[PDB]
């Protein structure tokens, strides 16, 4: 189900509620929106007032708002007014950069994984017609690359590059209420460290939560996968293999798990019930790819001038779909939530996009 | 090269493939930038420990690591003074036209022979395995090039001598 | 440092391989060809110089020249190029990793040996090397200690009488006649038949023809008479273009030049006469042993019936009171290489090598005193 | 240029420019120029005084003392006639042209003056060859070390003549290249029939130089050319003298030419390397 | 060769 | 008896040559260089790779023009050079054949245009130190050499360091002021039009306005400019109608000689007698990018430097360079500069009233000999100065630091 | 300066187009016709000379003459006129903008080549150009490096044996027989 | 042509 939207890479992707609209960063000072047309994709809009590079996008299932969180230490909350899109300036008080962003299930606040050693949380205010920003800086010691949220919206996990993957506890009493009892802790006030990684296991590039809110998993640059099971006495499970570093995290159900990265194709994992150990699953996407070429009498002589005439586009990665699918940027979900996920999509640094399935394989 | 160079090439190729992974990291220390981290040496947070793949005292290679770039430095197997001179001159002539390469540096690391450079800006606009293949191929072909240069200079000396002696 | 490489710079072919193997790993002719035309196409800046099987394949647009002529090198650039090719492209082994063994014909100028040693020690900086004789390696391959060697190569034919544990340097005879002169005479006679061949490509073609459709004649006059009744001896060969050439008396005429050098105009004697003279110059007692053992080697002695003719001629010349035996192993082509490999494998020879330190301190003249 | 020339073209050019306008009346064209050539010798052209009707040429030979001791009376009348006068600059041979007298020849005189350095250098070698030719008792061997720290020695005995060269290389870069260059000098003989024998020696100085205080050291090679009358007679004398005198600069220039050749070859190979690299960029 | 024969 | 150093002034046009401590550049030869190239087609992966000794089988200098089987290929193009191998070949040929100087025991000074990039200077210095092994080297802009040579015009004993020089060139003519030995770095402008494109325009017009010449012997026909055949013109249209009215006496004739068949061919001389040299003050004719005069550029560059130096600078403008040999050039430049400066002064006085009268600014153009070559004498005096032997970069400096010692430029600094 | 124009001065037809396209953008025969009658009507002062498909359409009152005969040009004015027409009216591209490529049959006189180069460099002042052979371009089009070419054009038929990376100039045969003789 | 054939 491969498709191409641009030769150059793409930074981040965002989708709407009906999976009919797409957001693609062209690796330039703008962002584009693509819409479905029968069985085809075509450009619809063109949003641009940012003079820097965009590196984070997200979508609101109900509010239909889009946030551009990137360089220039700024962030604009896009909203739809009739048949056109307009910006909404926000203030974040950042000095270095901002990469990743994420909204909340209830659409009341959004967080930015800023590169200034700080994590910012903001909420809507009608008084000054602005977006106020708070800061979390106590335990943070380096950049944060991945953020994920919990149903109640009070627990936040902010992966960083300091061997740690920590949950936080943010509660703005202005637009938040007391959450129900949770196994983790006490839902303490904003700006505090709840718990830290058990030990040093590589950096962090992604995080994933569960509907029951009792299991957290993340990946690392050290070719490792972790699963913090809080239902038990903070049982921690680990797994490793010879695969290249992963750069994404997501799971299907309470036991499944999915990930992708420089391996160029999806890799599937699973978690046991009581054994406290994971396992491995190989190329759940498909068996393998194929390769082809042509004579190209013009090319046979065109390539000899610069490259060798006998040379060609064939590569060892053609057989296992490792030729053009250069790396994987992140992952998303298609249907429902993180319970069944009948379909899953992934982003590619090649500048394209692709879709997959979880039941079409039919074991 | 099965019994002489094959294992060395395999090991260095595997190391490069593992360390060829790169990603874009917004500048953490200097306002807003995406400049290479290895050259700056600002934060030890991103840097990875150096590695070396070598089998003799006078020949060596170095493999660096970072989010933005990976740097590799080689040391050739030069024995005689003519070999050193020819290697230096050939590398200098390679430097003088390094702009078209888009991969190579502009001056070798101190105390070492030529070194290369990679970045996230050179990984998508260019293929991945082709670059490592080219680095390998250069490593093998250096000896051929130096031997060919040596025989060429010897032939030149022979021809000039023959041309002069005829007059007598 | 586990094994050594043995290279035989044959006058018409090069043999190389590892020390220990029973067969060579590289067998290509000594050809260094260069383009003869101008060149028009733009998509190829290819290899101004050509060497090896590549030269043989595309010989039609190249001026093939043999670097070695009658056992003595004439162009050093070509020899260095072939050495580099064999070491790198084919063997893919660095000179420093293992030492090299070299062989040369007897009674060669000292200048060639000194230049070869200097080039090997300076250019490739080999850790150590040695220089030997093809005939002694032939003895080693044959697993014998006494006999007479008939090393009739492509460029030189020579004999070296030997006895148990010692040699006779004063009874060595070297004859310039070899395969190249035979090929030239074959071309000349093929002209008399009606087929013309001048350039080097047709030289290779005639070389192949001789390799495939030549044999020796027990009796010259009887064979000529039977040729007068030319209805069972003529044979046909298929040229690359498809033309068919019929060869009759030429099959057994060119080989007879070895026994009758007067055909080419050389005022010398045949191989039988030279071997008889060499054996006679030896001591009386060792004559019996030399007669009882006659080793032959080289690519010019594979003609069927050569052994029988040599035996008949020697018995006719020698007194008819003893027994003369000819030994013709079916692998004499690579006997020199096998002997070199066996000699290198010998434990006692691990110290006879010549290293860089002693060579530099002493000088190129050391090889002269190293086993003559 | 392959065989380095012996005629300095600077004097030829300036004398041609002066003489082409000579027949134009009272035209002094005051000239005062200083030059330099191989062997570390300085030339000087300058009028003797305010009188510009006479032009003078001088030399600053390093080994001039040996020439004066030997005596060059042959050179004072054979090649140079009455237009030679006692030294002025530094006790070194200096000549002048008398413009008031009609100069009949134009090219012959300029050519004769062009080879001044070799013309004066030959005074010793030609005289030694005459000594061995005439049958006179073999004149005592002599050593002639010119401006370069190296040395030159010659022995003139009966039935043959000898010459030995000492070589010194200054920069460490060119030492090995020159060693390689001279290694094959002693062997290349397959294209010469009537040529002298050539040999190279660096570790062991020849037994001839043991007594003589010639160039002696460690990083010094030696080259000897054996001389015979077949290539040292009255016909093939000038050519041999020119070849031997221009030996040093010949080696130097061809070393630099080889350096340029290898530079060109590596520059050519860079293109092949770039072509191999270009396989990584997409279509 | 140098004298006699070519090589 | 110390040996003199060597003076060389390389460039796009006729390369000056000679030794230091002398009053006349002995050798003045073009940059033409021969080569045994022909028609191969594989010319971008083996440019030449001449087998054997054919690599050096090439001549040089005036003798290289009359070789009709090779290729005359100029290596330089208005300072910047594409391939420098030809430059190295020319340098070795000159030093050995013509100069006959041993690099290991001599000092070489070289001159380059001010716009030369640092890379070219660095790499040429590296080439010199590697191949020639010259003990010392020094590179400097040619303006100061011209200023030093200008002292010979009058009153040499009267030291006069201030002034400005607008030098010519085969492909470049630059403007550089001097303020008591110290020049201004930012007040330098590079002019692309020079004495070569002028001849291109001359021949282009001639190939249509006249016939009777062969394609080969075109430049020799186009070199009427170097003759008395070009005068400058205070007015353009006036002389145009003067020619179009009479067109009888003002027209000249050419009597060149063919170099192949030895057959005389003649052509008349028309409007090109002045248009070419007039292009200097109207560069828009040839180069469309640079639609900017010269005199106004001179005043602008002289008006972008401190007040105390503006006054003496206008008083000293040196006429040095081949392209400046045109007659009445100085009159036109002086008149234009005087007009513009007087207008500026009057405008400045108009806004602020006063019965005063400032002393008029004096602008004078000096005509003298040495115009063809003003860089050689500067290099001679450069070599003769003992301090040159001390400022020159040494071998050990290049040994490990690299060739960056020669990267110093007058318009750079951090 | 982004592409180049390739023009083939065929003995009976002219092919031209941009460098990169797989088909020519201009295919018209080489005809330079002039009126043969007197002319009476007054409302026409039209084009004393005619070229191209126009000449083919109104060929009934014109004396058609082929400028090129058996591969060698006979009238230079006609060739310059056709060049101007193709460059301006059809291609509508100025010569200065892009360079031009020219092809000619083998064993042609050097005078034709020199005159063509001089006219191209002087009249249209093209930035650059080149001269090649039709057979080698045929090899390039066929995507092969070895073979024998049978370039039987309208004016000349010739063969040029080739081998890998080199040609054989001493085995070139040119035959004047061509389509015109067949038509006669 | 000039000699042989017309052109
Ligand atoms: N099958 C053969 N029959 C007869 N002669 C052969 C045969 N193969 C090669 N030859 C001849 O022997 C020569 C090569 O054998 P070789 O021993 O390698 O020469 P060398 O002495 O230089 O090693 C060739 O020149 C060829 O003429
Ligand atoms: N007397 C002259 N009249 C007209 N032009 C001249 C005259 N002398 C030189 N030129 C022109 O000036 C140019 C040479 O100036 P020059 O600066 O010496 O070249 P370069 O820049 O290499 O030093 C020549 O191209 C020549 O056309
Ligand atoms: N469809 C056709 N069938 C047969 N012959 C044709 C056809 N079209 C053209 N021709 C012939 O080929 C000639 C033109 O082909 P062409 O290759 O363009 O000549 P040129 O080589 O000079 O360009 C015509 O003169 C005509 O005789
Ligand atoms: Mg043999
Ligand atoms: Mg100039
Ligand atoms: Mg045609």
Image (tube, coloured by chain):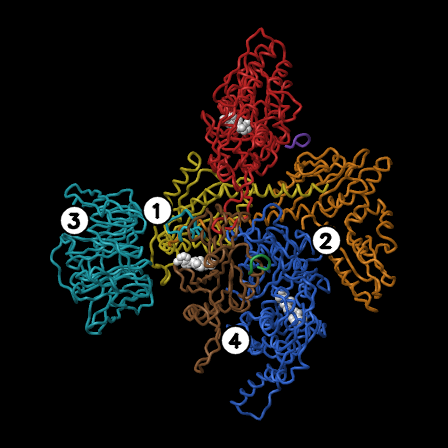
Chain colours: A cyan, B yellow, C red, D orange, E purple, F blue, G brown, H green
Q: Assess disc 4: are there few (<14), some (14-19) or many (≥20) residues with their C-alpha within 10 Å of its C-alpha.
A: few
Q: Mark 4 points at which residue?
A: F291
Residue under mark 2: which chain is it in?
Answer: D
Marks 2/1: CA distance?
Answer: 63 Å
Residue D121 location, x and y as percent?
79, 47
Q: Which of G51 and A49 is in front in this view?
A: G51
Q: Quadrant of the N terminus of chain B?
A: top left
Task: Locate residue A158 relative to residue C356 in the image: left or right.
Answer: left
Q: Name the residue under label 1.
A: A315
Element carrying mark 3: loop
Residue under mark 1: which chain is it in?
Answer: A
Q: Is residue C242 visible?
A: yes
**Are the residues flagged by discs 2 and 4 from a single subunit?**
no
Q: Mark 2 points at which residue?
A: D37
Q: Nearer the viewer, residue B106 or A155?
A: B106
Q: Residue furthest top?
A: C321
Q: Which of marks 1 and 3 is nearer the N terminus?
A: 1
Kindly tell me whether mark 4's CB lies below 8 Å from ligand 2.
no
Task: Locate residue C285 relative to residue C232 in the image: left or right.
Answer: right
Residue under mark 4: which chain is it in?
Answer: F
Q: Name the residue under label 3.
A: A359
Marks 1/4: CA distance?
Answer: 54 Å
**Are the residues flagged by discs 3 and 4 from a single subunit?**
no
Q: Assess disc 3: are there few (<14), some (14-19) or many (≥20) residues with their C-alpha within 10 Å of its C-alpha.
A: few
**Where is G79 relative to B114, above or below?**
below
Question: Which-is-in-front pick, marks 1 and 3?
Answer: 1
């Amino acid at each position: 189900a491969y498709h191409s939207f641009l030769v150059e890479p793409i930074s981040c992707h965002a989708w709407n509620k009906d999976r009919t609209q797409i957001a693609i960063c062209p690796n330039n000072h703008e962002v584009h929106i693509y819409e479905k047309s029968g069985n085809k994709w075509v450009q619809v809009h063109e949003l641009k007032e940012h003079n820097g590079q965009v590196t984070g996008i997200d979508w609101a299932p109900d509010s239909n708002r889009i946030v551009t969180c990137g360089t220039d230490r700024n962030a604009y909350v896009w909203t739809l007014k009739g048949r056109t899109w307009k910006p909404t300036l926000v203030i974040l008080r950042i000095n270095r950069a901002a990469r990743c962003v994420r909204w909340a299930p209830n659409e009341k606040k959004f967080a930015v994984g800023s590169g200034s050693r700080v994590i910012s949380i903001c909420y809507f205010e009608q008084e000054n017609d602005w977006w106020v920003c708070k800061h979390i800086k106590k335990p943070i010691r380096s950049t944060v690359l991945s953020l994920d949220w919990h149903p109640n919206s009070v627990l936040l996990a902010a992966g960083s590059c300091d061997f740690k993957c920590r949950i936080f506890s943010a509660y703005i009493k202005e637009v938040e209420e007391r959450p129900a009892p949770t196994p983790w802790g006490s839902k303490m006030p904003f700006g505090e460290l709840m718990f830290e990684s058990s030990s040093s296991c590589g950096w962090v590039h992604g995080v994933c939560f569960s509907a029951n809110g009792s299991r957290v998993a993340w990946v690392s640059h050290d070719s490792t996968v972790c699963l913090a099971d809080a239902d038990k006495k903070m049982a921690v499970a680990t797994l490793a293999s010879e695969t290249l570093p992963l750069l994404a995290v997501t799971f299907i159900t309470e036991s499944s798990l999915v990930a992708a990265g420089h391996d160029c194709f999806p890799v599937l994992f699973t978690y046991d019930s009581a054994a406290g150990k994971l396992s491995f699953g190989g190329r759940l996407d498909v068996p393998k790819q194929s390769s082809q070429r042509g004579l190209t009498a013009r090319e046979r002589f065109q390539n000899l001038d610069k490259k060798a005439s006998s040379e060609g586009s064939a590569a060892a990665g053609a057989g296992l779909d490792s030729l053009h699918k250069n790396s994987v940027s992140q992952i998303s979900v298609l249907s429902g939530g993180k319970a069944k996920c009948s379909q899953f999509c992934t982003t590619g640094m090649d500048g394209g996009m692709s879709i997959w399935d979880v039941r079409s394989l039919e074991s | 090269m099965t019994a002489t160079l094959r294992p060395y090439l395999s090991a260095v190729r595997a190391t490069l493939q593992a360390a060829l992974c790169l990603e874009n990291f917004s500048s953490q220390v200097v306002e807003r930038h995406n400049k290479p981290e290895v050259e700056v040496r600002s934060s030890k947070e991103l840097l990875l420990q150096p590695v070396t793949i070598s089998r003799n005292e006078k020949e060596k290679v170095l493999i660096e690591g970072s989010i933005n770039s990976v740097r590799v430095s080689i040391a050739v197997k030069q024995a005689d003074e003519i070999e050193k001179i020819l290697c230096h001159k050939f590398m200098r002539f390679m430097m003088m036209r390094a702009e078209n390469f888009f991969i190579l540096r502009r001056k070798p690391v101190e105390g070492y022979d030529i070194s290369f450079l990679i970045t996230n800006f050179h990984t998508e606009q260019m293929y991945k395995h082709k670059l490592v293949d080219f680095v390998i191929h250069f490593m093998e072909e250096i000896d051929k090039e130096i031997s060919e240069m040596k025989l060429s200079v010897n032939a030149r000396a022979r021809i000039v001598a023959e041309e002069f002696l005829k007059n007598f | 440092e586990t094994t050594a490489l043995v290279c035989d710079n044959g006058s018409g072919l090069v043999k190389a391989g590892f020390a220990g193997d029973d067969a060579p790993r590289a067998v290509f002719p000594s050809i260094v060809g260069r383009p003869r035309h101008q060149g028009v196409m733009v998509g190829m800046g290819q290899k101004d110089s050509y060497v090896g099987d590549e030269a043989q394949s595309k010989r039609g647009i190249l001026t093939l020249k043999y670097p070695i002529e009658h056992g003595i090198i004439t162009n050093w650039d070509d020899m260095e190029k072939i050495w580099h090719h064999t070491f790198y492209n084919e063997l893919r082994v660095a000179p420093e990793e293992h030492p090299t063994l070299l062989t040369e014909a007897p009674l060669n100028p000292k200048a060639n040996r000194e230049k070869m040693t200097q080039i090997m020690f300076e250019t490739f900086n080999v850790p150590a090397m040695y220089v030997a004789i093809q005939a002694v390696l032939s003895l080693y391959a044959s697993g014998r200690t006494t006999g007479i060697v008939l090393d009739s190569g492509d460029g030189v034919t020579h004999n070296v009488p030997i006895y148990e544990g010692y040699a006779l340097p004063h009874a060595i005879m070297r004859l310039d006649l070899a395969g190249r002169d035979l090929t030239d005479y074959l071309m000349k006679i093929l002209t008399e038949r009606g087929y013309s061949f001048v350039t080097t490509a047709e030289r290779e073609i005639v070389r192949d023809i001789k390799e495939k459709l030549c044999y020796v004649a027990l009796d010259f006059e009887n064979e000529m008479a039977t040729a007068a009744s030319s209805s069972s001896l003529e044979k046909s060969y298929e040229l690359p273009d498809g033309q068919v050439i019929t060869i009759g008396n030429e099959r057994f005429r060119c080989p007879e030049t070895l026994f009758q050098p007067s055909f080419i105009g050389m005022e010398s004697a045949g191989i039988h006469e030279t071997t008889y003279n060499s054996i006679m110059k030896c001591d009386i007692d060792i004559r019996k042993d030399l007669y009882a053992n006659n080793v032959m080697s080289g690519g010019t002695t594979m003609y069927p019936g050569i052994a029988d003719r040599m035996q008949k001629e020697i018995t006719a010349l020698a007194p008819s009171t003893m027994k003369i035996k000819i030994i013709a192993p079916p692998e004499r082509k690579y006997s020199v290489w096998i002997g070199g490999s066996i000699l290198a494998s010998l434990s006692t020879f691990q110290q006879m090598w010549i290293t860089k330190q002693e060579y530099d301190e002493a000088g190129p003249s050391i090889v002269h005193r190293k086993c003559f | 240029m392959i065989l380095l020339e012996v005629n300095n073209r600077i004097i030829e050019e300036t004398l041609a420019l002066k003489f082409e306008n000579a027949a134009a009346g009272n035209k002094p064209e005051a000239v005062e120029v200083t030059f330099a050539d191989f062997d570390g010798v300085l030339y000087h052209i300058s009028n003797p005084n305010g009188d510009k009707t006479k032009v003078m040429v001088s030399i600053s030979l390093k080994f001039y003392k040996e020439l004066q001791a030997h005596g060059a009376d042959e050179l004072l009348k054979r090649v140079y006639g009455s237009y030679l006068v006692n030294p002025e600059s530094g006790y070194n041979v200096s000549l002048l042209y008398d413009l008031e007298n009609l100069p009949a020849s134009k090219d012959s005189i300029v050519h004769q003056a062009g080879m001044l350095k070799r013309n004066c250098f030959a005074s010793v070698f030609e005289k030694y060859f005459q000594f061995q030719e005439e049958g006179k008792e073999g004149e005592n061997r002599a050593v002639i070390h010119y401006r370069d720290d190296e040395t030159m020695y010659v022995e003139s005995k009966k039935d043959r003549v000898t010459v030995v060269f000492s070589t010194v290389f200054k920069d460490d870069d060119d030492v090995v290249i020159g060693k390689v260059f001279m290694q094959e000098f002693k062997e290349g003989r397959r294209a010469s029939h009537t040529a002298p024998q050539v040999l190279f020696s660096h570790r062991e100085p020849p037994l001839e130089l043991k007594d003589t205080d010639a160039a002696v050291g460690d990083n010094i090679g030696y080259i000897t050319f054996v001389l015979f009358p077949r290539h040292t007679n009255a016909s093939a004398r000038d050519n041999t003298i020119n070849l031997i005198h221009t030996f040093r600069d010949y080696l130097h220039y061809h070393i630099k030419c080889s350096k340029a050749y290898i530079h060109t070859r590596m520059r050519a190979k860079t293109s092949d390397f770039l072509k191999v690299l270009n396989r990584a960029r997409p279509d | 060769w140098x004298a006699x024969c070519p090589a | 008896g110390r040996l003199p150093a060597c003076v060389v002034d390389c460039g796009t046009g006729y390369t000056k040559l000679g030794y230091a401590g002398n009053t006349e550049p002995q050798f003045i030869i073009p940059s033409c260089i021969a080569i045994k190239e022909s028609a191969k087609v594989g010319d971008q992966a083996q440019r030449r790779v001449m087998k054997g000794v054919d690599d050096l089988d090439f001549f040089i200098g005036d003798e290289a023009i009359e070789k009709p089987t090779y290729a005359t290929k100029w290596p330089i193009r208005h300072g910047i050079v594409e391939d420098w191998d030809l430059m190295e070949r020319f340098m070795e040929q000159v030093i050995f054949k013509y100069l006959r100087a041993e690099p290991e025991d001599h000092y070489f000074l070289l001159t380059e245009p001010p716009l030369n990039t640092p890379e070219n200077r660095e790499y040429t210095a590296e080439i010199m130190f590697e191949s020639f092994n010259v003990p010392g080297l020094y590179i400097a802009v040619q303006a100061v050499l011209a200023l030093a040579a200008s002292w010979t015009s009058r009153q040499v004993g009267e030291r006069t360091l201030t002034g400005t020089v607008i030098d010519s060139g085969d492909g470049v003519t630059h403007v550089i002021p001097v303020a008591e030995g110290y020049v201004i770095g930012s007040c330098i402008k590079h002019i692309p039009i020079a004495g070569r494109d002028i001849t291109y325009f001359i021949q282009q017009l001639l190939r249509d306005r006249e016939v009777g010449i062969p394609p080969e012997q075109s430049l020799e026909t186009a070199k009427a400019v170097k003759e008395r055949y070009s005068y400058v013109c205070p007015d353009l249209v006036k002389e145009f109608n003067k020619y179009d009215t009479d067109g009888s006496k003002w027209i000249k004739q050419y009597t060149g000689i063919n170099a192949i068949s030895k057959k005389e061919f003649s052509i008349d001389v028309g409007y090109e007698r002045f248009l070419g040299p007039e292009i200097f003050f109207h560069p828009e004719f040839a180069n469309p990018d640079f639609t900017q005069p010269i005199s106004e550029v001179v005043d602008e560059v002289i008006q972008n430097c401190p007040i105390d130096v503006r006054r003496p600078l206008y008083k000293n403008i040196v006429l040095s360079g081949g392209s400046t040999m045109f007659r009445d050039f100085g009159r036109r430049l002086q008149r234009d500069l005087k007009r513009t400066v007087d207008a500026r002064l009057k405008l400045s006085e108009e806004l602020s009233g006063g019965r005063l009268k400032p002393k008029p600014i004096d602008v004078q153009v000096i005509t003298h000999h040495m115009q063809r070559y003003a860089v050689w004498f500067g290099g001679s005096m450069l070599a003769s100065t003992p301090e040159f032997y001390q400022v020159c970069h040494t071998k050990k400096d290049y040994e490990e630091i690299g060739p960056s010692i020669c990267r110093h430029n007058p318009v750079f600094g951090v």
